[PDB]
Image (cartoon, rainbow over all chains, first blue to last red; front, side, top):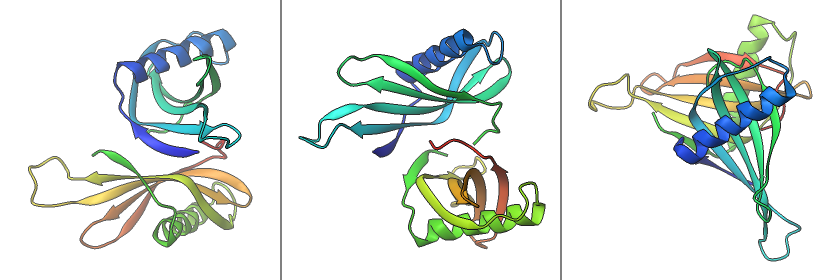
Length: 96
Length: 96
């Protein structure tokens, strides 16, 4: 799996909002309020069982500002289904 | 400062050893044993907001395996002097 830096544009911001919505359902922090995704944003492209360079899915690692704190969110996106899941929502973490 | 992905070659490994040595002088995590810097490794150029008489320095964010655990390290390197400062050394953290 190859890591790359990605932009913190609307698509990335919406992943941050998804992470905070998923973290609110888990409830470890009580109700968080999404502010913004900050740099750096990174994306890993995960390859399936090697039989074409076929794409399995993507992992995003985001720094998410919510409720005056910073969190590290790890999100998985399935290439075939386009379904997303929150892998990890941890913090507060110090800024990069 | 735009973040970029960098290699985990000898220069990166030696930044990880610097971080572990600095973290040992603090002692928050007891005496750690440097294992390896893992992917992904990231680097930002520091300007000190000017116009461009040159590069001031670099910030690195590294995942450092030490005493079989994983830690996130933030390091500053002066461009001219090559003098280094541990900004942050935290964990254990889950893999990226």
